[PDB]
Amino acid sequence: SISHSASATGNVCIEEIDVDGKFIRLKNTSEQDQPMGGWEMIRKIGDTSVSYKYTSRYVLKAGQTVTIWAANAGVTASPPTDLIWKNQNSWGTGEDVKVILKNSQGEEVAQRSTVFKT
Image (cartoon, rainbow, N blue to C red):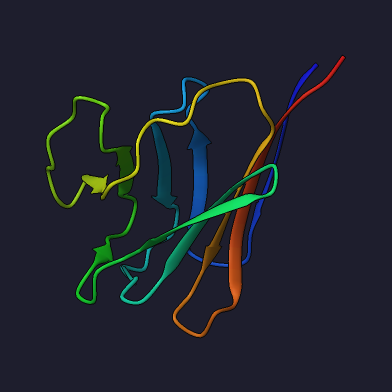
């Protein structure tokens, strides 16, 4: 029914796509701090893809998580754990979603999908 898929080649993975459509959470599962300056997160739903760009000095430290919140989720920025997706509002529920993570060289280093199926 509700099905999950995901993979990563590096230190950072996409941990969760909020079923409620209010956040995407990532985690550094490694023992290495991960510089993410210039990194890009892409959310695709249907024909539409929306980009988030990590700020230049952003670092996801070893074992830590980062939650990227919809601008209307009612959450205040709290770096480094909680960041806000500028001008991007919560995106609903129940439509297939795929998130891809790219490094500064544009290489896909992680991905996660949620698929709903009958």
